[PDB]
Image (tube, coloured by chain):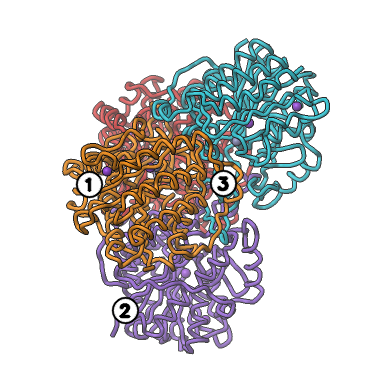
Chain colours: A orange, B cyan, C red, D purple
Amino acid sequence: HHAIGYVWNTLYGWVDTGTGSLAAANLTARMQPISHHLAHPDTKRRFHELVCASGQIEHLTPIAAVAATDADILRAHSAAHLENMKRVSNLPTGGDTGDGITMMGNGGLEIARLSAGGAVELTRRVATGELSAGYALVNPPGHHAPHNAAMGFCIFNNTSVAAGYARAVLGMERVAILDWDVHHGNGTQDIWWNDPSVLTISLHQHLCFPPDSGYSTERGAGNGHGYNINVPLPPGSGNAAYLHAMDQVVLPALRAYRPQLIIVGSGFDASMLDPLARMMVTADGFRQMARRTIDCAADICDGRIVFVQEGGYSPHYLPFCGLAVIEELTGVRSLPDPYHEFLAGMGGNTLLDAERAAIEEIVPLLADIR
Amino acid sequence: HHAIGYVWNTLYGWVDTGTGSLAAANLTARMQPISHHLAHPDTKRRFHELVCASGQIEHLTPIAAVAATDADILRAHSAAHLENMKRVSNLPTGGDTGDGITMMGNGGLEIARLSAGGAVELTRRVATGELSAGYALVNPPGHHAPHNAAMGFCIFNNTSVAAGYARAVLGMERVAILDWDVHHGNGTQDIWWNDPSVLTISLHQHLCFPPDSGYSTERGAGNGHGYNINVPLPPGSGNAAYLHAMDQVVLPALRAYRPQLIIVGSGFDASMLDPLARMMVTADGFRQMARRTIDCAADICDGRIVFVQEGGYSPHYLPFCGLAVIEELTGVRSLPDPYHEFLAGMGGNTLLDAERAAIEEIVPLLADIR
Amino acid sequence: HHHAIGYVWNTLYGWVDTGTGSLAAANLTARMQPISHHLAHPDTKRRFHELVCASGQIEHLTPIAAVAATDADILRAHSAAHLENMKRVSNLPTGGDTGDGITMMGNGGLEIARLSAGGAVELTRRVATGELSAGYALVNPPGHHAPHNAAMGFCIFNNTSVAAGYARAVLGMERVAILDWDVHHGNGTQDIWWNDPSVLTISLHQHLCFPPDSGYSTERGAGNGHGYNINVPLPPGSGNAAYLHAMDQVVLPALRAYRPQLIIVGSGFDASMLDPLARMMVTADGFRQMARRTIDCAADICDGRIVFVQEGGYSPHYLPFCGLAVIEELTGVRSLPDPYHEFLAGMGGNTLLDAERAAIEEIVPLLADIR
Amino acid sequence: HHHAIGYVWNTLYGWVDTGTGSLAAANLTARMQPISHHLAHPDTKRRFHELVCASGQIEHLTPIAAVAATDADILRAHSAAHLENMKRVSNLPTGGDTGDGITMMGNGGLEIARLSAGGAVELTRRVATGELSAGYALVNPPGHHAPHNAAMGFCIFNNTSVAAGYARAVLGMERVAILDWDVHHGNGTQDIWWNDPSVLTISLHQHLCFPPDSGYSTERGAGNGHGYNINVPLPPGSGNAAYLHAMDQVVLPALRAYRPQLIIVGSGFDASMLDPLARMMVTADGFRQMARRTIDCAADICDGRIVFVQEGGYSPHYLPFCGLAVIEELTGVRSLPDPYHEFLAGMGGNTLLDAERAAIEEIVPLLADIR
Ligand SMILES: [K+]
Ligand SMILES: [K+]
Ligand SMILES: [K+]
Ligand SMILES: [K+]
Ligand SMILES: [K+]
Ligand SMILES: [K+]
Ligand SMILES: [K+]
Ligand SMILES: [K+]
Ligand SMILES: [Zn+2]
Ligand SMILES: [Zn+2]
Ligand SMILES: [Zn+2]
Ligand SMILES: [Zn+2]
């Protein structure tokens, strides 16, 4: 009852995000090439390197990624999508996958399989009881990829591949995916839209990405009606809003649902220094969010909780946000956040009326979780 | 009555911001070295290169920076501060100047003089009527440096050196400094605190940086009481809030004061993609802010307006925010913002109640501007 | 008698997209990890430009705007098929490799290739008219590997050949010389003017460095052009002594024999002591002396009409000082030391070795065939 | 008879702060522009580590944790004054240059220097006991330029000498050999063991590349150590043929004459064809053959006890493949091609030139003095 799994694969740091900023470089638009795309793998690699350099790695059980099979991927995705990803992976320089901001390098399907497979392998080992919990520091991310496409830097929906494995292979009847990446988990929402056996929750900045989704009225359909929960929050929301959302909506939803496994889509792009959103969460905020969620798992599903890396785009600060979560898993709290004092005076630590109201909009939906 | 000055010096791109993220790299804190400090000069250089590549440079009059003299600097700063900057500039690898986030490279005083001097030289040429207006794309920035210190990446207060020159050398009785960098212009506020001959205005994110300043109650002292105006805005404020602040506070303040010259501390760190603040301004927002301010100058001080670069930390997006301002100066609107559609759906375009109220707090202070 | 030195830099020369590979593209199956800076990344040449400015040399130069090379300009050196193929790759959403697997063109990159060739043309025009006495076109992408019908070795169009073709067809010059001291064989230039005695083509290079199968002393042109191509392959490790002996024994005598009306220098700095893409030992003082000699030769034989056009060089650290030395020889304002001078001076290359002397002496009997 | 190959990598080896200069610090008066990647930046060696993992070689290796070198460990190779001076610079808020103007230590960087020396020690311990048959310590910062009383040439402590001193004093070995094939002269190692015949020190290097005044064949040790230091200076442009001739004629016979109980290899890859900091032409296949020969020699004379310790190498592009070749010779699993092989193979270096042969033959008469 205490052994914490940790997945990193070298190839997670070799994802080729190209020479553009977001979309590709384009001379006619006068978008100058740049060395580091916003989604460049160094951000997540720096998190891995801090896990090692901090000494946290000594308290973790390293777990090798095992490449996701076609069968694994097909539990979350269409055969057509999988076949299309094989095609672009073959291109001599890779290329965009569909949406104009989602570059796959040459041979990049290998990395996408290892990323989904890292989530699956950790899930397997936690669910069997070999491990009590873990963190899969994967790349590329997953939560934007719906059933039939790649989208928003995501090739396959890692957490959904892992949930599908938990359902079909491990025979779990109820799984929860809690996504706190600052962007709406539209892919995950899509995949399990009609399905009450995977409760999908997304805490995000309202309309940050994608532009047309993540409204509280998006609640699933058919037998899945009531088993998708969006918590859109306003720009500028910080630790107070995020913790109020955890206490009023997320944790009660999990307790109502009684999942046999909790998977956390753990992005750190809600951080105070992220370029790709406008939120004010600090490493201490993420710490408290993780502590609450792990304690919830202890109470309702024998501690079975798997964290899977989603987004986050500050190479400076993301490592300390991620380390705080790892420390809550290991219980070894051995390094300060060196930005703590600098960021703590910027605010986000008072629950504003507009933040409170956004969260309260979701509370009446809890009663529909049977 | 139409000739637009433009200052860039190669050395503005050679500022040595070190190997840290914000503070220096530190092994005991496990702050890993990184190639690009948040304040790395490539951000501003990319703006310069876009000015050239877009063809805007063909509509601009290039103006060489002339190094600020000791006498120039002393109109804004103490002799002790100037002498201290000579000392750290001599260090073999340079070093921090005081506050732990303000690195000067070896020989870096040369660049700091050229940065202040770029502001002065443009000011001189606009004020004499050789030029109608201009943009000084300087680096290092200025607005955090108070009378007796360097602070927040700023060695000398460029806009205050330029205002002091306009006062003492050109004999102007009234100058305005309008700072729309997202961080509080505490340095500028300090320098002219007791002085009604330089009206200092700062539109900023409340308590973003520095942590203890920029409150609406900071209004100057003695004869300068009423001649400093802070407009702190909440995190998440976008184009609607910024334009409401321009229309309700900034432009009326300028009209009340009747400056003979307007200097704009033109930062783009309020942009939607900036890591160092939480605001939602787009290039079209900055465009409208610039258009309004230039038109105000046409109405009240014969078009005499000088823009001087302050902060901004998105190498991806800052160039397009800066280009929009340049286009409003030249009147040649020849390149789209390629991020426009991507960013426009994220919000910030509706004036929220909390934003409106923050701005309305400053309106009663307009009556004290004589 | 006149002194005005032209200088071409265009912002877009620094925006060339060399991709995320090292040399070829990144490739996961081969386990070639992506990297930020390709060997040929534009920062190397941009750092040279920035040093020209920061050193104060720019104050002694006459800035000359690049004018995009027209289709007609390009067709004086290249086939219509090559030009049309470059339009195709330039249109791709992320650009792509042109023919040879190491020559990436970015999206819209044809614009930069036209400005690069056009920079060489515009400087050539203004020197030839006498507006300028001489100049330096700090262009990018480079040119000398591109033959008539292809892109090759980071080169889209052969800038110096476009400029020579302009000097021939538009300015009516009967004799032009292209002296290429890039460390790699100027195979493109050799190819373009192979049959043509009106452009004397000379290449000083490391033997078999790049391309693998060319630059032998036996490659001398054909037909009426026989004798009007001169290769000077030198052994790896050759330094200042060898390069200067080659200038004195072969290059300068060749130019004097030929009596060009204009000298175009393919000015690469990849023969430098710190270059990753060759094994030569030339220092900034070596390049200085090479430039001084060539400029003085131009003064003697073609009224000072000399145009330098940037080719290769891959040390972002040291190339700027090698380039600055050449600029200083043009302006006559020698105001900055090479800060690497003492560090590099003890490594050698300053004695003419027997193998180096012999390699150079192989070319001397060919001088008599230059009529 | 046993086969288990140790491998040392520590995350902090990739965190060495080489600063914002190219070689020396950035300097505005000299107009040396700041740059992101110093020549010695840790990404080069990290890319080697990442390729070891991504290639699947890591699956055939036994990972061995670095253990920080103690003061006592360091003092077997260095003075107390040097150790104390390194504590001082490590304490500086942004670190700083150590003695020589090109050797930057970051803030807290002594921690990494201890882990680097300690990685060499720990691998040496585990090979010597027979737990492991051999191994590779991919350490950083490097060691071989650091003499007894100073840091020099990117080196804080002399890792291989700390390891040899441990093998002598703690493991009681009477004879150890250090074979340094970094392209720069191992002057530090030479200095440390100058008077001492119990550590045979051999350096194959480019003549006068770095440092400027050392590595001559006449530098042979002193007193009881006379004859127990062997320098093999080679000319610029030397490639696989020269390096292998040096191995066969000098290095391997020296080791056989000496009968070390342990062989430590100072394994640099800065002799590679693409290195900016030297002018040699060795390819990954060259390094492969050098490693195979040395490992086979160890098998014959000291029960296979061979420890490789990373020294220099400055091509982030190519070093990983040179290093991988050596790892493959240790594991016997030859599963990835050198993707540069065909590109580099035609550049030369594969014929033994007369000057190269003569440089090597100068050392052969010194073999008889190794008793
Ligand atoms: K669902
Ligand atoms: K989310
Ligand atoms: K004031
Ligand atoms: K402000
Ligand atoms: K010819
Ligand atoms: K050549
Ligand atoms: K010895
Ligand atoms: K050596
Ligand atoms: Zn996200
Ligand atoms: Zn700012
Ligand atoms: Zn070349
Ligand atoms: Zn070396």
Q: Looking at numbered disc 3 in the image, what kind of residue is underneath it?
A: Pro
Which callout, 2 or 1, points to the residue nearer the camera?
Answer: 1
Residue D80 in view, yes or no: yes
Which callout, 1 or 3, points to the residue nearer the camera?
Answer: 1
Q: Chain of mark 2?
A: D
Q: Does ligand 10 reach within 8 Å of label 3's beta carbon?
A: no
Residue A145, compared with residue B161, is above or below; it is: below
Mark 1–mark 3 Cα distance, whole angstroms, equals 48 Å
Which SS class for mark 1?
loop
Query: Residue A29 location, x and y as percent?
Result: 40, 27
Mark 3–mark 2 Cα distance, whole angstroms, equals 46 Å
Which SS class for mark 3?
loop
Q: Does ligand 8 reach within 8 Å of label 2's beta carbon?
A: no
Mark seen at residue D34 = 3
Which callout, 3 or 2, points to the residue nearer the camera?
Answer: 3
Q: Looking at numbered disc 1 in the image, what kind of residue is underneath it?
A: Ala
Please name the residue that numbered disc 1 is placed on. A76
- Given contact means CB atoms under 8 Å apart, are the residues at marks 1 and 3 in contact? no
For the residues beneath circles 2 and 1, the answer to whether they share a chain is no
